Figure 1: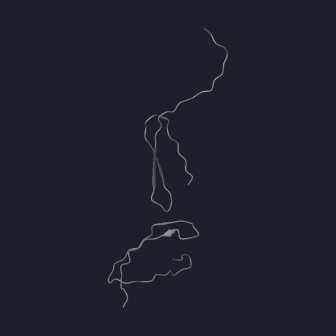
Figure 2: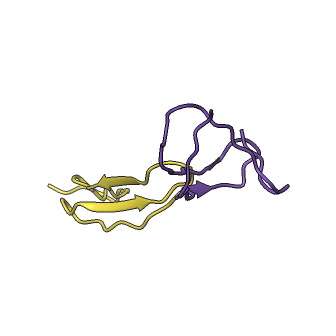
Figure 3: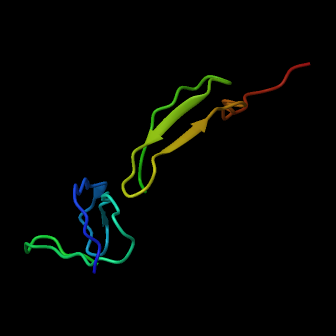
Length: 49
Length: 49
């Protein structure tokens, strides 16, 4: 039922040593069908908001 | 944001200083001087007519 995408051509933009949200990473992809998808890290270094 | 520069003292010469600051689009400043009077101090010895 959810979006089934591939070729996840992502990237980064710029990064700071803040304590709040000061690392911005734009990421691109191909839309197969519009919806919503949830993101999550898989290591302990980087949290997401 | 603390940033310094070294500009020349010539009337009308347009000087540019570029600032690479994080988390924002970079910035450009321009400055030019016109009336750079060297007003000296003074003292007195006597008069004459």
